[PDB]
Length: 67
Length: 67
Ligand SMILES: OC[C@H]1O[C@@](CO)(O[C@H]2O[C@H](CO)[C@@H](O)[C@H](O)[C@H]2O)[C@@H](O)[C@@H]1O
Ligand SMILES: [Cu+]
Image (cartoon, rainbow over all chains, first blue to last red; front, side, top):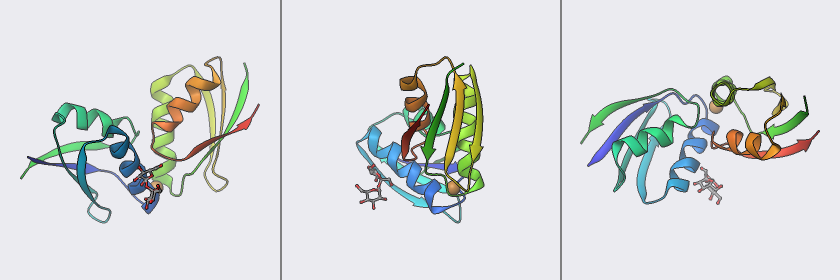
């Protein structure tokens, strides 16, 4: 499944930060849309693991669903 | 009591808010964030190690500017 999250990013540095923590987690295929403040992820990790990883950044995060 | 200074690569207000949230979550800290100068000052008993690790959770590039 491809999980979609709303992540409050407001500059390229914000997106870069999200990319860095997801890479640290590893085993992820993702794309970040800055203007629409959305991050889509595909991985063997649980939704909870992904959510916690994103929330640890200090940014506002919410789960939108999956495709 | 110790007063630490860190360099944090923040590039927008949202970046600063995220740093604030991770420090608020850690607790036991008195901090000041200087966005334009990419500097975060922290007065805390928490070890330099703990503070560095906490700031790194933001996914931003962090370095130590000393006591
Ligand atoms: O610290 C490595 C970590 O940084 C990220 C954050 O987006 O990527 C940036 O740094 C890379 C250098 O290794 C650049 O190639 C890349 O373009 C840049 O965004 C993570 O992707 C990477 O794991
Ligand atoms: Cu930002």
